[PDB]
Amino acid sequence: QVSVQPNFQQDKFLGRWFSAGLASNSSWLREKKAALSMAKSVVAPATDGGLNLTSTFLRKNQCETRTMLLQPAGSLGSYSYRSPHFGSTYSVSVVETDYDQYALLYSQGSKGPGEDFRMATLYSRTQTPRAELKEKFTAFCKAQGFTEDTIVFLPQTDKCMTE
């Protein structure tokens, strides 16, 4: 029931994005909300036709890297992620993007212990998204049932943002 960007162009969605906003129903994320930081996420074509999403972010005086394989899931812009640690499966969709400024992503658990998880993410090409982009993200999060207290604009940073 999740919308996907019409005529999604995977070749234009590649490269460097910044995670500029987050909303979720995770008890963990809410507990850590104030401590959350902007991540740098690099998207590259994967060998399966989908995408590798490599993220780097500051956590407790260290730069952490995570890699997520997004496998094609039936339509362009619709992907599946399988957690290698828990086996949980998630649908991850590029809901709306203009490729050169922003993307709205929506992730929802499918099978396993993560099945109840839901999360919206604002990706931005710059670290300082304009008010109109932030209000766009707020609008999507509210339409999807996230409450004000679970929506956060992730504060920008020098840490872990370099190449």
Image (tube, grey):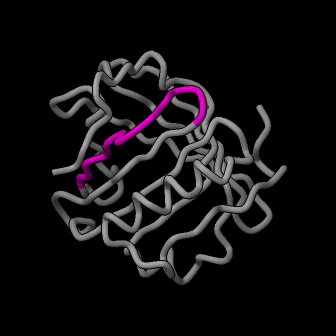
The C terminus sits in image quarter: top right
Q: Is residue 116 left or right of residue 36?
A: left
Residue 71 appears at what percent x and percent y? 28, 32
Number of numbered labels in the structure image: 0
Q: Nearer the viewer, residue 17 or 69?
A: 17
Q: Nearer the viewer, residue 46 or 79?
A: 79
Residue 135 in magenta stretch: no
The stretch of residues the image draws in magenta is 89-101
Q: Residue at x 41, y 69 (%)?
A: 24
Q: Is residue 88 above or below residue 117?
A: above
Q: Residue at x 76, y 58 (%)?
A: 62
Q: Residue furthest front?
A: 132
Residue 63 appears at what percent x and percent y? 73, 52
Q: Is residue 152 above or below residue 69?
A: below
- Per the picture, the main secondary structure of the magenta-coloured stretch is strand
Q: Nearer the viewer, residue 148 or 84?
A: 148
Q: Residue at x 67, y 47 (%)?
A: 129
State the image quarter where residue 93 is shown: top left
Q: Is residue 10 left or right of residue 158?
A: left
Residue 159 appears at what percent x and percent y? 81, 52
Q: Is residue 48 above or below residue 117?
A: above
Residue 44 appears at what percent x and percent y? 50, 24
Residue 100 in magenta stretch: yes
Q: Residue furthest right?
A: 158
Q: Is residue 113 left or right of residue 63?
A: left
Q: Is residue 8 left or right of residue 156?
A: left
Q: Residue at x 35, y 56 (%)?
A: 85
Q: Is residue 76 above or below residue 105?
A: above
